[PDB]
Length: 218
Length: 220
Ligand SMILES: [Cl-]
Ligand SMILES: [Cl-]
Ligand SMILES: [Cl-]
Ligand SMILES: [Cl-]
Ligand SMILES: [Cl-]
Ligand SMILES: [Mg+2]
Ligand SMILES: [Mg+2]
Image (cartoon, rainbow over all chains, first blue to last red; front, top):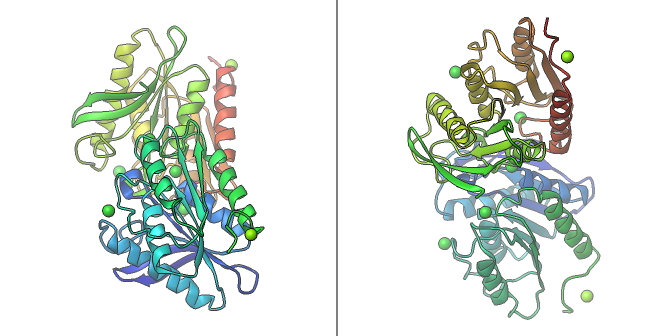
């Protein structure tokens, strides 16, 4: 499972589980900013990785540049977006017949994930856990090209409800996607004491999506 | 509260504080990993340790070391963080002057700082050291370790391998008058990925047994 691949700033370290099935969808999992202790082994990041793995995806989580054994210097976002595109290119190189992808990102990783979504038409679903629309600029989502899940806590002081609600309201004006927006009572930015609750919602969301629900009629 | 700011040697230290409902309640201080491994006071294992002591009636504090979150100052190899932990313990004790006992629980780098605080502070009668790194940080100051406690590590840990943890535990087990409870969790890495429930169950069982007067040697 331990892998090293090349990104624009040098080596990027990752954890990789190929699907046992042919042409399986790919999931890329993206971690928080190091100011909030983000790495590919944060529990929420690991649990996201595990959720996709258990549902038969080819799955990759990885450390952004400067984190762990990943080379380079952390930057405001452009480099990390480039890292994420490199990581997806790498898994796709190994799985050329996977035709679809999901991205799941937590905190800063949700911002990078939604930027990747905008650039990569094969990404047909996303999860954005605790996005920070008062800290990072999400106006590039116009329109958001895919249905997905936004999940945040009502005790979050880093990215408050009012801010997440404004982003979701803007997205919900876009015909042809469904934004599933769950707010968890008592969850802070780190979902302290609420990780099981968070992961059960992400699991339910993915199961319903794999059943063909929670997207509009095309 | 529970959000608190108190003064450390390097400036402001940010914490989360839950006082006990009870009188003379013991104090628990919870210490987080190094920032290279994403350590903050809100790491899930750190939070769960905090919540364990909270639920068992302890006055409980977790906090961010200097440079982490809103805590001021620059991170250093360990001396500063030990000073931070001492300041943190002094602060809680200033608010709870009738508490006569304390536990420290630390994860990774936090376990090394925790055991150093244990060595300095006679009121500390128990500890938990989750994923200690005796191949990276020097534990040889434990001479002897003054209290019984729990060391818990995983057998898939590549940061601090089993052999290294076992060597520290074997050294401590030569010291009479304490009991080192050492659990090795199958399949757990340094981050207990997919094993946090298992880890926290073992921590809970250990504290429950210790509060029942078990897992410490007889008075003799
Ligand atoms: Cl974590
Ligand atoms: Cl921005
Ligand atoms: Cl928060
Ligand atoms: Cl050292
Ligand atoms: Cl490890
Ligand atoms: Mg339909
Ligand atoms: Mg006895």
